[PDB]
Image (cartoon, rainbow, N blue to C red):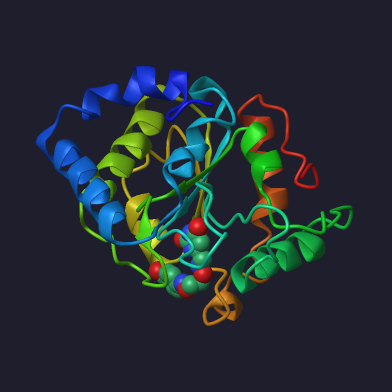
Length: 223
Ligand SMILES: O=C(O)c1ccc(/C=N/OCCO/N=C/c2cc(=O)[nH]c(=O)[nH]2)cc1
């Protein structure tokens, strides 16, 4: 395997020599010497491994990785087999079931099948100390993932951005609405899901928007 997918590296490596990025790398490395940090190194950049950067169709922006054992693996909201889907992911699957009648629950929480279809599952902060939510907040990841969002905004066309919650909406605030499609709703967490996420129908809406972009739809059940 590779640490960082080649097509993504080609376009994002301009970040790597910048002072914030050097500092970020040092911070994460030091944290790993004293704490268990999730995801493990080989999974920090899973979101670069699943499809070519040129083939991104949909972008779902997250915040912090899961902080429990075996959960985070470098794709926002996803958990690898055999880990049970956390409540936020169960809510995502519940909305899918009501939104698209023909959706089939895969019986696991691994969203790799979406990533392979060009659904970028990007957290803003890409590491977290075990059991400590937001422990790596504002250490440099935000600037890096802002650079990712900026690259896609400028160099791709007709993407669908799904911005769930106020944090994601802020991170996507500068997306050019004349050049990309943006859908917004509340966050799927249990505390916020009934404040707009249930009933948002973003999955069916996304596929209709992809038609306008001249692109084939996501098969949301291909998991
Ligand atoms: O800004 C808001 O409106 C808002 C509201 C509620 C929340 C809540 N989060 O609660 C934790 C739920 O689980 N999240 C998992 C999770 C896993 C992952 O890979 N990425 C990720 O972004 N989240 C966040 C933002």
